[PDB]
Image 1 (cartoon, rainbow, N blue to C red):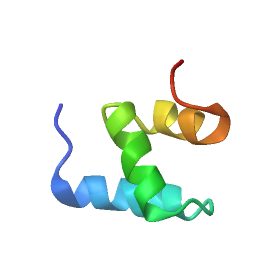
Image 2 (cartoon, rainbow, N blue to C red; image 1 turned 90 degrees about the vertical axis):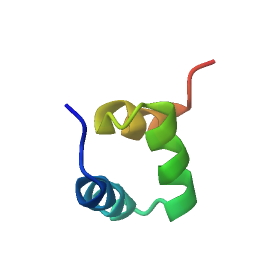
Image 3 (tube, rainbow, N blue to C red; image 1 turned 120 degrees about the horizontal axis):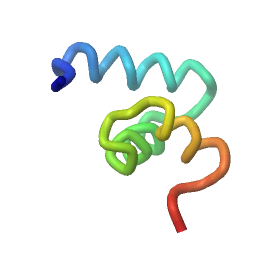
Length: 49
């Protein structure tokens, strides 16, 4: 499964609604390979390492 670009954008804006700035959410989605659960985990408690 490959999300579409519009699905990516709604995933990004949805996580941004928590209060996170756009660029940080973009980086977290890259770190998590577009898994929103890992991305939010990274935004809450840090990226791996």
